[PDB]
Length: 214
Ligand SMILES: N[C@@H](CCC(=O)N[C@@H](CS)C(=O)NCC(=O)O)C(=O)O
Image (cartoon, rainbow, N blue to C red; front, side, top):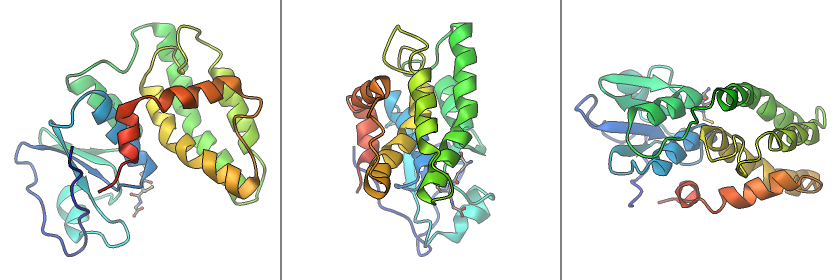
């Protein structure tokens, strides 16, 4: 796959609502990365076109013609532009071909909703730590470690790979090296299920490719 160029304030607008599916992203936004990973994991590279924008020098046509809330990601599909990364990974999973990324088992679904609900707290805990407000990252990763012990039919949050792993991957990807650098803190220390989860995620090529750049 060829990753397309970043569009700036000086870029001409793409067709909007011409029938092509477009995923508007920033190459470094973790929320957008969630959706990009979902696209790749479902083999949708030829179905969903990436439209990367520069958030520091962004095209006015984005807010004006594509997505008024003026954030990434947003998904243009079937004459609607929709936002919210968690909504979007669920939407793509259920409206496009490719392997299903969400289990049918009601108990796994229920646990998944607990974990989706926890994403805000997870980010807040880590950010609190980086900002020196409270050392909450350890407790947050303890929660993750415990969650990984719930289902023993695979190494991922719901046992087998799912949208839940995808939701967390961009954030763990960023928090891990930052905690090591800024707080001299290794999240894998004492957290074997988490260490295994990171190793297994890193074997997923569809995810690794979202760490790529033009
Ligand atoms: N709740 C949104 C968050 C999206 C978001 O905060 N994106 C940021 C980049 S990390 C953004 O587009 N910032 C640009 C701005 O606020 O103007 C989601 O889950 O998709």
